[PDB]
Every structure is written in structure tokens, then in C-alpha cells.
Image 1 (cartoon, helix red, strand yellow):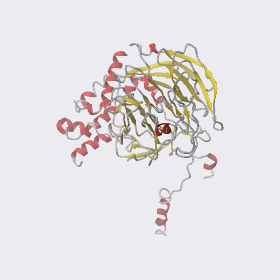
Image 2 (cartoon, one colour):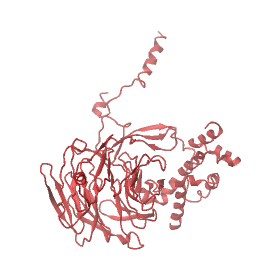
Image 3 (cartoon, rainbow over the protein chains, first blue to last red):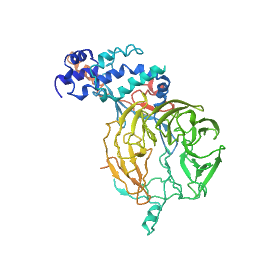
Image 4 (tube, each protein chain N blue to C red):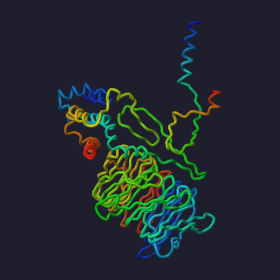
Length: 159
Length: 333
Length: 52
């Protein structure tokens, strides 16, 4: 709860990846300690790959921003058609939530400006010896990231 | 929060000393988005539409009618129209797509039209658009149709099922409109999830993914448009988000097959009804298996349905057939 | 006259963020193609804005 391990996983929530990679190559058995230190090397890697993944599986996900639409709350008496009202709050937890009436977005909105997404395949075969050799057999806790790398690989042979 | 009993003639049937079978069966139940009507359907009984104005349930009994869709065939599902409050698109089993009107001033029900496109073997699925601008009538045997409602009920295009998948004679168990009204999510027999583009009048498939290895029983949608939840004949009930079309949660509570899925209008509780007469509730935003309640139902087949306006709990499952309505269930013990 | 100046500079700052009376945000919806609304970018009418 308190100490170095909380420091080492609060630096991954914001943006600071270069010190944490330098630590976890010195002492690799800093994992098996907290299960939360593997979920935050997955949220960084999911940002660098989501522009890539939506380009190969393009026309499905391009219509899936047209699929992601909400129901409009109508009235019975005068036959109205009204949309929904949300609120935007700021918290300290990195993963996005959505309550009964409000959304919870991360407060530090410029967290990703150090990082850069990459090109088609010749960087994904280069940015994986760095990041995915740290969490080697630990992508089983991030099961969505294991699908998005393999859905690239089937859509790369078909293309 | 108190137990209050539902007052139809099904409670009078069981209260008498009638031995063999008091009501018979329930075929379909659909809500209009206004959240004051009901389409309570039976097998050989009555399709009873309801209109209760202010009280909980003890205000008035509206209408029961056996001879509504005729006297020889049955109705698979009753689609309500989002545009017209007085319109319910009932599709009979063999060859009838009739369109009925209801009257509040009189104890009757009149019919506006009965349109039919020929060589109709068996249409079992009819459902309008969430905005009410299309009607996709889909057979489980040959092909899927597409009509309109805003001008009239006129055909535009149709697609044959064998162009979607290519394995065998597959049955279409359940399909669901998208939430924008622009896509079709259809559920096959061998566990295929195919996505069809239905913008205005063109019907073309986008992609097909292998959800699991069983008949995909139900497909529901989230009112905030983030994800969609599927069911199975296995124990699997995945939660697939829409921006990436991958899986997020897994409800692995494999004690039986899955029959009925519902969500809430806020999108919090997922209600799963299995085949061992056991119901569950879960959470969507929270972790995988975090129950709020489990309830043992009696010996007969129940049904589960959620209101579109406010969270009120409709179950069935009395001694032969009766519905139960649980009032003020924000905590549920 | 300087000790009366900084006393009223604080009262000016205490009237811009901390008391700060706002309008009664009444929702106005015309386009059925947005399906969602946030109550942080509601801009009022121009005949009410130019008076204010």
C-alpha cells in the first residue's frame, strides 16, 4: 500500500514509462507482488496499438462509432423525444467508469503526450521486445490485449 | 418494497379446485418505449394488452381476447411501433402479418390492415427500429426481408441467409437491431455473430465472428451504447464492447443453459434466467461474477422482462403460470 | 487608504468563483442525431446573453 511499489505503479498511471522499464529490467521479480502493476503496463500498450488496430479492421469500426449511440428517453403524454444528460467528473483512478448519471474521467488529461502510437508492423515488432518482455507470461490478466494483437495478425495475412 | 399479487384471471384459475392445467403457456412479451403498455401473449389463451394509468396494478383490468389473431393459428412475437402509440404489429404463424389498433373508450380491438408478401412460409420474427422507421421480418428457414413504416409498409430489399454463412442449414434463433438503428446483429445456430448493414434500404453483411460453440439464444443492448451482451446454450454470457468489438467481462456461472437476458435502463444489472429454474443478477461496470441476488423459481418455465422507463421487476413463475411484479426494488435485500 | 484597497481586492476575488450565481439551466433540444447532452457547454440565447 505504501512505499516503493506504490511509487513504481503511480508512475505508470501518469506517463512515466522510461524509469519503470529501467527498474523492472534490473529486478524482474518485482512482479508476483502486486497484480496491479501488470494492468498498467497493459493500459500504456493498449494506447500505442489502438490507432493501428482500427486501421486494418477499418470499415467495421468506422461504422462502430455510428453503432455506439444511445437510446433517447421519450415521454408518454405529449410524445417528446429527448436525449440523455450526463456529467463529467474527475477522479484519480485511471480506468474510465460510468455511474447512473455521470462519467468518471482521469484528471490528468495530458498523460499521453510523452507516448506516440506507431506504424503498421515494423514498429509493433520493435515496441514489443521492450514492453512485452517485461510482462512476459502476464498478458492473461489483460485478456483484451491478447485478442487485439491476434486480430491484427489474421487481418495482416488476409490483407 | 412488499410482495403484491398480480390480478389477472390466472390467479382465479389456481384458486379454484381445478386439477389438470389452469392457464397454458406464454409466447412473447414486448414493451413500448412509453412504458405504460404491455403485450402479454399466450399460446392458446389470450394476447392481453394492458394500460394501467396511475396505480401499481390494482386499478383496472383492461382487455382479454382469445379471438384476436383468429381461431386457428398462434402469434410468435408482437412488435410495438415507436411512432404510433396505437399500433401493434402482430405476426401470426402461417401467413398473416396483421396490424391491430386498441381502443380505451370501448371493450374491443380493431384491425387497421393485414398486408402480406407472398410465398411466406413462416415468419417468426418481427421487430421495428428503435426510432420506428423500418421493419425487418426474418424467417428462420429461407431469407430475411426489409420494409418501411413512415410512408406505408412497402418492401424494399431482401437477403438470402446462405450468403451470410456457408456451413449448413442454420437456424436463426434471435437477432437484434442496433441502438442507432443502422446495423443488424444476428445470432445463428452454430455460434456465429454476423453484423449486417441496414442504413435505409440496403442489406449487406460486414463481418462474422465466432462467439462460442452453441445456439446463441438472446442478444441485448446497453442503453449507453458501450457494449452488447450475448447468451448461450453453454454457460457463457460474454460482454462485447462496440468501439473495439472484443470481450470485456465474462459471466462464467456455468450451472445450466441460458434462456433469457435483460439489462436495466440505466445499464447496471444483467438478469440471467437459466434452465434449472434459477435466476441471477450481476453488474456490468464492476467485475465478472458479483451477484446481487439469486432466486429459486418453482417447477414451471419462467420469463423475465425489464420496464424501459424505471427499474421495476417483472418475473413469471407461479404454480402453473402467473406473473409477479416487485415494487420499489432499488435495494433487493 | 492602502489597507482599504487590499480588503476590497479580496472581496472582488471572492465574487468571481466562490459565490458566483448562475442561471437556471433549462435544457433545449432540437436535433435528434446527438442522443447525449452534457450540462457544461449549454450556451443561452443571444437576446439573453447580450443583455447580460
